[PDB]
Image (cartoon, rainbow, N blue to C red):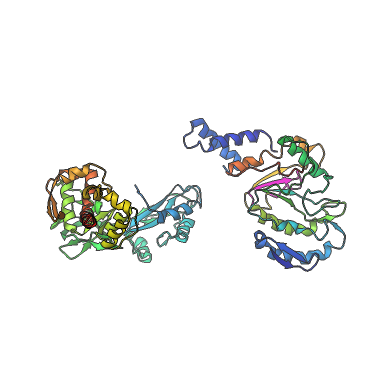
Amino acid sequence: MNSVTISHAPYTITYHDDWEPVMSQLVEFYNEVASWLLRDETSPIPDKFFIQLKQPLRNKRVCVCGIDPYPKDGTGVPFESPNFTKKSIKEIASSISRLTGVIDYKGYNLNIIDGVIPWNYYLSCKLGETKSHAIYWDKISKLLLQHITKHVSVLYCLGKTDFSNIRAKLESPVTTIVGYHPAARDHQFEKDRSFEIINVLLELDNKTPINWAQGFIY
Amino acid sequence: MTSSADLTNLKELLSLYKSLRFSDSVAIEKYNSLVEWGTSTYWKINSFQIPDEIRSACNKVLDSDNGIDFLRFVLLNNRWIMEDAISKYQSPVNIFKLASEYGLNIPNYLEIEIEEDTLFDDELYSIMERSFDDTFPKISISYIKLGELKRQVVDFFKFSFMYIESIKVDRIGDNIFIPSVITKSGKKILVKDVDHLIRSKVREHTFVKVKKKNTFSILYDYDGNGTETRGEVIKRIIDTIGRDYYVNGKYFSKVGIAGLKQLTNKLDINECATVDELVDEINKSGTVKRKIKNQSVFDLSRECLGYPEADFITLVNNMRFKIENCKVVNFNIENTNCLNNPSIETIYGNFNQFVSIFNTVTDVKKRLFE
């Protein structure tokens, strides 16, 4: 629950203890970048970004890396939406309901499922476009990911071409596996099974499955 | 890029991975090939009872590399001095450091980087011999080449005949002793345990083979004309050591409070350092008193020492005794054949402890129903 004040917006960083071996430098990398970031409005707004570092790292069992934040009205929570309007969460709930068996459902958000970290790789971007802030966040990301990958023994990257080399951008032979964007066309979540292998290498590492049903709203 | 096929391969790995212990051959060969494939896709696929002081650190350093199947310790002077472990991929260079981090005695690792495989000579071992400073009697100069899982072993020595005059004990720890063979020429000679001493047929006032080395000199195994059966040796040495020591494990130990200790153990009570404390603890314990009452001093003082049921009797029925006040003061075995049985000599060497606990239980049983 520790805090540090930073140079620019939002001026405050409230990190859980699991994130303390890195917060030291995250401030260093931020003060020399933010002055540029905030020259334009962004989404999620500056009051977000690091929301998901107050969450623990020891309770976590898989992490899901969506390279990008929502180009139109995000909330600082990856794939999240209050009225189930956005496509990524839509298709994710679809291909999960496909295996669970219940298809009558209020809403969905991937955060509360125990063992999953919903993660962005670029912590924000300009409004209406994507990857427009890759020049700022790069080492920030690299650092967050080195930290997060030795807590969780799995990696599911969303993106067939963007997570193309990250094997070399991580130095621990973690179980890194690549997937495809479901919001993308050719119906890529129709041609890939993305789960049902999660609680399998969560098996061979002698560990508990993932509770894919708890994220449903009713 | 992930399909159902990989799923099938990993499912077979799953099923037979912990049947690998005793699978059938095709399973083991399939596993050799699927550890192969999955590693690039799924990245995961005459020693005796060592008490726990060492087994805890063993359990930790065996987590350093799962190629580690055992640890190799040299037992010396009542110390477990590790030298390496049977690892399959991890060179022991981290392993002796680890074992040092976990409370395992390691040696003075002074390893000369060898380029061309060679065997050490006069200096080549002597100088390392000074640099080592082995307060432990380890005489194997072995060098690990990194890049292998074996060693290069060098040791040179002589042997001759030494004239023993008598045999001794020598305290090494808490209540523990060793034999130091004393020679007619005023020199002391070492041995490993009691059984090394036995196997030797060691006696007094004669010459025997001894392996003489510069830093240590060790009483050489036996090779001569053996007509003196084992039991005779056992009896002789048991008398020679004295009536105050029994044999615990590889070593001796004086008879003492350990009697009260074991006894308090057997009757589910508190430690009692003196005998009247004991009688009190029994007397206030109606159940313990009432479960003594039905018993005999003999059955009880042999159950507190775990002799099995019977061969104890083949022993007892082979000696004569000396009793006053229903209390053993002396005894002596007269037929030596039974000692040639293994299960018999373990009881014989461990006797004076039994005598003492017998006198004690006699006394408490007297004073209790007094």
What percent of the width, then of the height, locates residue A21?
65, 62
Q: Nearer the viewer, residue B239 or B312?
A: B312
What percent of the width, then of the height, locates residue B117?
42, 53
- Is B96 situated left or right of B158 in this image? right
User: Does residue A34 appear anywhere in the picture?
Assistant: yes
Q: Main secondary structure of the magenta part?
A: loop
Q: Quadrant of residue B137?
A: bottom left
- Is B169 situated left or right of A45 in this image? left
Q: Nearer the viewer, residue B285 or A86?
A: B285
What percent of the width, then of the height, locates residue B350?
23, 52
**Residue A76 on the magenta segment:** no
Q: Quadrant of residue A107?
A: top right
Q: Residue at x 47, y 57 (%)?
A: B93
User: Does residue B304 appear anywhere in the picture?
Assistant: no
- Location of the C terminus of chain B (image quadrant): bottom left
Q: Residue at x 36, y 55 (%)?
A: B74
| Magenta stretch in the rendered image | A150-166
